[PDB]
Image (tube, coloured by chain):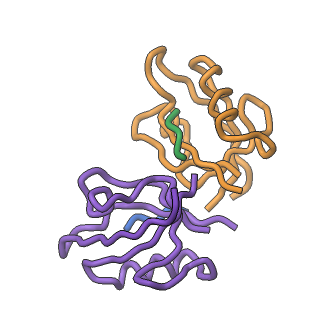
Chain colours: A orange, B purple, C blue, D green
Amino acid sequence: QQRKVLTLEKGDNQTFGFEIQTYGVTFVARVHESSPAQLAGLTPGDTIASVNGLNVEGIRHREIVDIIKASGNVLRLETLYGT
Amino acid sequence: QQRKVLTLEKGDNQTFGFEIQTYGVTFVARVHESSPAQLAGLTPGDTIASVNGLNVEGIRHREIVDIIKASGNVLRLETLYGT
Amino acid sequence: SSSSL
Amino acid sequence: SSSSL
C-alpha cells in the first residue's frame, strides 16, 4: 500500500530481529518471529526509506547498519512496500 | 567471487528451501538450514542469473517462481554474488 | 513480495 | 551481503 511508519523497541542484549540487503535501495530479507521487528509490523519485501527519521537512499549498507547498531534499543523506521 | 553453479535436489513433498525477491534483478532473501538449497551452497545475497539453464534477467518474478515450481525435485541454478 | 520455494 | 540487526 502507501507508506508505513513503525517503531521497534528491543531488549538490551537482543536484536531487533531483521536482516537487510542493498542493491544498486535497501530492503528486508528476513524478519524473525516474535522479534520487535515482526511485532512492529515489519515485513519481508519492505524497503527502508528512513531510519530514526533519516533517509538512506544515498547511504551505503555498512553505514545504514552502523546507524541501526547505534540506535540503542528503540528504533524508528519508515518503509515502503518493496516487492 | 566469480560465478557459481549448483544443483538442488529435493524430496517429493518438500521445498528447495529458499526465498527470492525481485527489484527493478532477483536474489535470495533467505535459505533454510538443512534444505537442498543450503546443502547445495546457496547463500543469502546471491542473485539468480539462470534457472535450469535459462537466464532470468528479463523475466518477471511470478514467472521465475513458476519455472522453479515446475522443475520437479531437481533444480539447476546459476548465481552471482549479489551483496 | 518474497516467494518461498 | 545480508546483515542481521
Image coordinates for residue B67, horizontal then vertical, percent:
43, 83
Image coordinates for residue B27, horizontal then vertical, percent:
53, 62
Image coordinates for residue B70, horizontal then vertical, percent:
35, 85
In this picture, is A67 found above or below C1? above
In this picture, is B45 found above or below B76? above
B14 and D4: which one is in front? Answer: D4
Q: Residue at x 57, y 57 (%)?
A: B82
**Total marks drawn?**
0
B40 and B72: which one is in front? Answer: B40
B65 sits to left or right of B33 = right
Q: Residue at x 68, y 58 (%)?
A: A1
Q: Residue at x 68, y 35 (%)?
A: A64
Q: Quadrant of residue A2?
A: bottom right
Q: Residue at x 74, y 44 (%)?
A: A49
Image coordinates for residue B79, horizontal then vertical, percent:
48, 67
Q: As drawn, which residue projects farthest toward the top?
A: A12
Q: As drawn, which residue projects farthest toward the front?
A: B2
